[PDB]
Every structure is written in C-alpha cells, then in structure tokens.
Length: 126
Image (cartoon, rainbow, N blue to C red; front, side, top):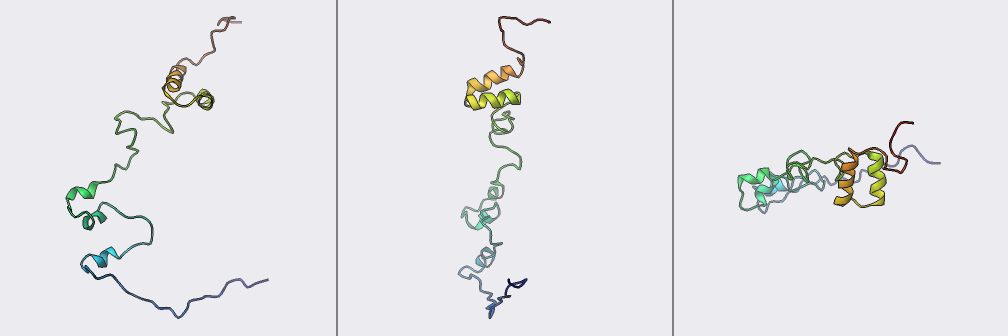
C-alpha cells in the first residue's frame, strides 16, 4: 500500500537566468530553443551561412509530395510504384515476384485484361 501522490521534490530551486554573450547581438537570440531536435530552418540559416543570400529563406521543398512524382513531372503514383492495378492480382503477384518493370507491365495489361485464361474449353455461354 502507498499514498495517492509522491513527494513534490521542488528542491532549494536555483532559478538561474544565464545567457551566452561572446557575440551578444546574435548569441542572445541563438541561445533560445524549445528543447527539441528541430533546427536549421530557412530563417535560422542567416547567421550560419556566411554568404547570407536572400534565397536561403526558400531552401525547403514544396509542401506537397514533390519527390519521385512532381520532380519527374508526371509520375503521379500512390502507395508504391503501381498505377492502380487490381488489388487481389497486384498483392498475389507482388509476393510471388519483385516490383521490377516486367511485373508492373504485366499488371498494367491485366488492369484492362481482367478475364480468365485461354483454356482448352474456350470462352462461351453455358
């Protein structure tokens, strides 16, 4: 058995307010952080890149899924390399055979050619 809350453990509380001042015009700003790994933003570059050119404020990619799609102009694929070929056929064949150009080509034909194989009994009514 134990109590509903632990000790508050606040300590003698040093409450320090120290700041970096070797270059106090910049260092008083550069010392500020939200204590996360996130850094090297397009504005944050201006003291770090000594060339200090305006274009550094726009170094980031577009907010969209630009890579392997819009850079390629028209490679507008989704979830993987596929162009929306039928899921049951895609998933079965992808387990049997890696996603190389012969697999994707055959399934792009299968997307149109959905029917049964050319068996000896032939295609007809009952």
